Length: 123
Image (cartoon, rainbow, N blue to C red; front, side, top):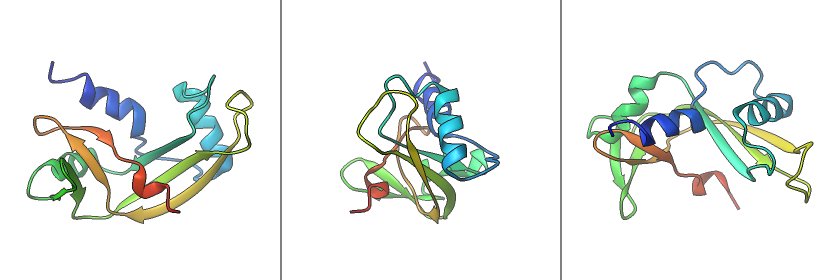
């Protein structure tokens, strides 16, 4: 169906209006979206307009990146939550990192179904 993935993706990485973009916000949204027990070691939420996000999938806001992905032409506001400590069990310990940059996504029939996170593990 022309949902699932696109719709899973939104549930996973989309948050239009984040209140705080801090540790507190990271732990509260993570717990709330149900990405704990055991906690996801890393996760980024894209903030902003949905339409612009969808355009990354066309040659209008995106470009072929790597073998089969697409990098955005425009920049986005984003918040990355990285689990820390050494225990993936609650209380989950997250550290928040806010940014503004281009993003890489996977598209499937004109729709994004995955937010690639390798550019967010900046080593």
